[PDB]
């Protein structure tokens, strides 16, 4: 009967999409990876993103991050854990990009802050893929969402990110970071 | 903290999550089109590293599934941009086992390839430095490969199942051998 | 003034394209990588392949392998040399694909045989990229060549591979392997 | 056997091969659009491993170049399929240093970004496990980053040049600092 909502969660056995949502079982494409990333040059993910947009003709993509997250912790620490270092170097660039903002916060609160920046940045990445641009620019309906789940509090009434167009992607992304920067 | 890594297809019809009779939080999931493990795919090899090294998983399960979008698309003849690149890896497998699959009926192929695919992905899994090393340092790691027959409801052990490189060769070679009955 | 011929050689300080060819300096796009591969899911290469076909509008791609080659040797040996193992696992699949044929040859002669299979297989890969298919199928001129260079003998008057269309790619590829199999 | 690894752009105008005044056979070349080293790029990281570990190279040079196809295409606004994905990494760099590049003239950006790019690729190079490890086992490895100004004929030391992680920080930070004169 076909799925209508793509979820991109973290491999960290978190965002049991199934369970966190509770919508219609069978209408949820899922992809999971360490720190729930959308990297410009990742076939794996983009391939999913493609199948979901072009083929299954989906109109929603949630990227969902979470707090107390292994990728983020791994990303912030130094242990060279092999391949995963490469993968997380992308997250470390995000940390550098917002170093100033993060660069003044109880270090405890930094992991959770970075979890949030990240969800914004991946939506921003997602939104700049040819896949998605093409789709919008050809008049197809597609909405993007960035949410952060916490095991204690549920979903944070945060600067979510929300993008239904190239123009809205921008505002949203900016607003998101703008909003996170206040302290 | 979880003992299994599940590697499923993005196609939505395999919710291992309950299927099994195990748990969540004991389940560390990665899902991608056609449920592949590609030699040079950082996305997935990354999931497999965190699994094997950080969490110290004991079982990695690759789960294929019948009438699968990915599999069908692979044999379809029509460009879908990026997804085609990703699916060429499954075409290579298709060609590999061509004779076998010619000796077969057009609509029955779908399913066969689904099986073969699982076999082949496990062989890929088991040749990764990651896995070959868990093994050499004597970590307990078993690799399992199943197809979910969405039609009959039940899963199905394909009996690829490996615990070492030697046990990897035997299952793989035996599986391919068996799928030319 | 623009280039008209893409060369894909081996990173093994071999196929100094420049020098091996001697055509018009400035009209040679080059990419090099270990064992001179064209992998289905490699952005790096495909990106070059794209720039060259779509943008610079090239009409020739040589993939050039060579004999006594580090990638091939590495591929055939067992030392786990880290990342490169992953990369070469692709070459090892080619070895498995032609195991029977290789599987009866003075083991010395195997490395050179595999060097040749490889050049065929990469052309075959190249030829099945959307990039190239799209190009042909839209009536653009594009020729593909697979040659093997030897330091002692120069270019082997071998089953080269040669493909100007989807249909010719096939014949050529088959003919190539067919031809290599005789002993 | 060779002592240098050269990492150039595919754009054809940088034939390091003679440019230098060194040699071939002492030169192990990898060329790709916009002369990038991406964190998760197996193609290139592979060249860099073979270089550093197998051949035991002493110098890795990343060479950018003025009016570069890749750089221009990055700032162009027009989809070119796959190449766009690859070029988003250079857009991210562009944005990163946006203010600097706004404070600048439309046609002069081209060149600046070319410089910045080199700076940033070297920083990428120097954060790879591969390189960070050569260093910890005390191998001699220096990383250099140059722009070839095709117009004036001459190369140009950008004076990113690193021999350790600490020496990597200093050059990088100093370079960016200097390119906001
Ligand atoms: Zn996580
Ligand atoms: Zn499927
Ligand atoms: Zn070579
Ligand atoms: Zn260039």
Image (cartoon, coloured by chain):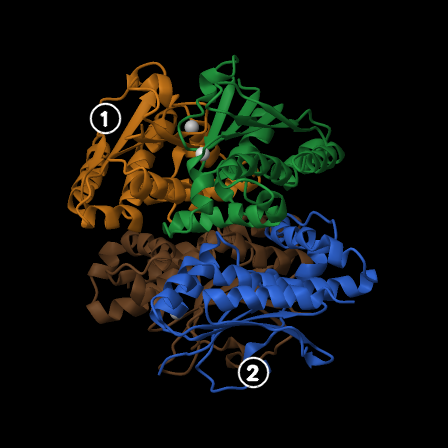
Chain colours: A blue, B brown, C orange, D green
Q: Is residue A10 visible?
A: no
| In the rendered image, the vertical position of residue A112 relative to residue D23, given as above or below | below
Query: How far is mark 1 from mark 2, CA to CA?
Result: 61 Å
Query: Could you say where residue A158 lies in the image, as x and y percent from the top left?
Result: 67, 75
Front residue of this view, candidates B123 and B167: B123
Q: Is residue D74 above or below residue D135?
A: below
Quadrant location of the C terminus of chain C in the rendered image: top left
For label 2, the residue is: A21
Placement of the N terminus of chain C among the 4 image quadrants: top left
Say left or right for A146 vs C61: right
Is the CB atom of the residue marked by disc 2 within 8 angstroms of ligand 1's nearest atom?
no
Provide the residue designation for mark 1. Answer: C158
Mark 1, Cα crowd under 10 Å, few <14 / some 14-19 / many 20+, is few
- How packed mark 2 is, by other alpha carbons closer than 10 Å (few <14, some 14-19, many 20 or more), is few
Picture quadrant of ligand 4:
top left
Check if mark 1 and mark 2 are on a common chain.
no
**Residues at discs 1 and 2 in contact (Cβ within 8 Å):** no
- The verdict on label 1 being within 8 Å of ligand 3 is no
The image position of residue B68, as x and y in percent, is 35, 71
């Amino acid at each position: 009967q076909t799925p209508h909502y793509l979820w991109i969660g973290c491999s960290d056995s978190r965002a049991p999409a199934e369970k966190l949502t509770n919508l219609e079982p069978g209408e949820l494409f899922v992809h999971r990876n360490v720190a729930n990333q959308v990297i410009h040059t990742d076939f794996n993910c983009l391939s999913v993103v493609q199948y979901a947009v072009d083929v299954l003709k989906i109109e929603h993509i949630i990227i969902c991050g979470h707090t107390n997250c292994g990728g983020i912790h791994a990303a912030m620490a130094d242990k060279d854990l092999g391949l995963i270092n490469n993968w997380l170097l992308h997250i470390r660039d995000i940390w550098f990009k917002h170093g100033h903002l993060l660069g003044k916060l109880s270090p405890e609160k930094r992991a959770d802050m970075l979890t949030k920046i990240n969800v914004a940045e991946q939506v921003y990445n997602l939104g700049r893929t040819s896949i998605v641009k093409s789709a919008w620019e050809r008049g197809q309906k597609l909405s993007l969402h960035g949410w952060v789940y916490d095991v204690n509090d549920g979903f944070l009434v945060d600067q979510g990110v929300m993008a239904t167009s190239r123009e809205t992607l921008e505002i949203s992304y900016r607003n998101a970071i703008a909003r996170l920067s206040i302290l």
